[PDB]
Amino acid sequence: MLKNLAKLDQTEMDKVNVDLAAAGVAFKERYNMPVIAEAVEREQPEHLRSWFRERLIAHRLASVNLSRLPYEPKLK
Image 1: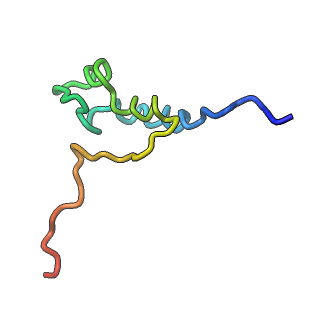
Image 2: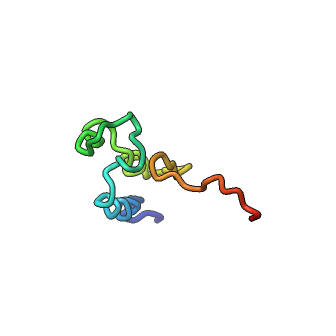
């Protein structure tokens, strides 16, 4: 009548990709992780935030380490 397999769970396909990129460290300690990555996942992986909440990441973006958009003087 109005149904079909696959309700909605493809977003992971894009996450399963970046999943190899970062593990949720460089992104943002999140919980103030030490100079380790195996602890970032063992504790609380950032990605998991979207990899798990993918259902509706919402907000998005963070910037904790990278840090962009300085305070240039502009205008010579």
